[PDB]
Length: 176
Length: 177
DNA sequence: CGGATCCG
DNA sequence: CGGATCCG
Ligand SMILES: [Mg+2]
Ligand SMILES: [Mg+2]
Ligand SMILES: [Mg+2]
Ligand SMILES: [Mg+2]
Image 1 (tube, rainbow over the protein chains, first blue to last red):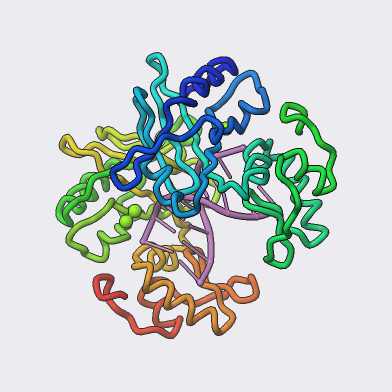
Image 2 (cartoon, chains in turn orange, cyan, red, brown; image 1 turned 45 degrees about the vertical axis):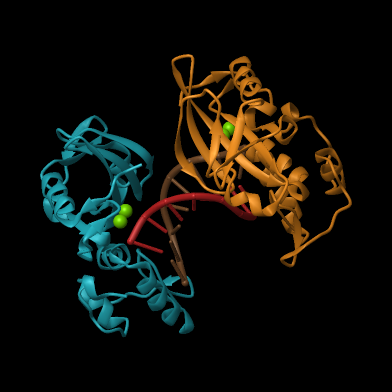
């Protein structure tokens, strides 16, 4: 995939928001715009992007085997590089140029943890996770864990998660 | 994605590749020798249909690992790179108007028997062997035999010698399970 | 830092 | 079973 400007990425996401769907045992099921979250360097508002990252919120665990492996994009030329239930990397054609589109899935209960993970940047996550690891925790895209057991946090949004974990809330573009 | 191949098709592809593999080392084209190219995977196990072609490249110096697969060259053959690093490089190659997957792996000379053992498989066989060794506080991989994170210096050269030294019955590749 | 998908 | 490359 070629590199994109921030505005090019935003235009691609805008286009994709009404055109994502998946095939579920022969039935085309549309993915709702409210369940599509821009993540990665695009959410961090970086001037150039290596690719476009979208997080898809899947409402039922049983649908994970169907969503990314049978992903459909109305009107758009694409091919699949690698694809499973949780990550699907596509090469898309946008105005005669090839760009990389990375799709990820989260369940509703994972959403704040997934948004936190997929926003990055990697350096920031490593720091946060190292600090939590010193206190016998493990943070990932699915939850907060201690002794391989989910720590049930009373939170909904990414902001609530970050503050509950004991860190300073920063907007995506100021996380470093 | 790559299409499936017959055993003969795989063998023909390997035969062709044996004289045509090289790599670029700081602007210098260095040919890979046929003696340092080993057919591995399902091709070595003589399976009737193959999902891809697996080659193990024996690299004579540790310093070359950063150069070999990341600057791989194949004379005359159309290919593209899917994923690539120092130890694994997956290519899609064009062979008689069809696309196939070619998987290249690297081993150092001292790793050769271990690498051949690993890359021959099948997976079920390796899991069984490794589970048994794990019970005795060993760890076997493509690079060596280890105990307490330390290389167990075995006095062996070939894959057959390794298998017997590990305490297992030697079987030819096609009879491993 | 931690996991996904892939490699035998 | 154990590791590589790539994902944030
Ligand atoms: Mg990205
Ligand atoms: Mg991406
Ligand atoms: Mg193979
Ligand atoms: Mg292979």
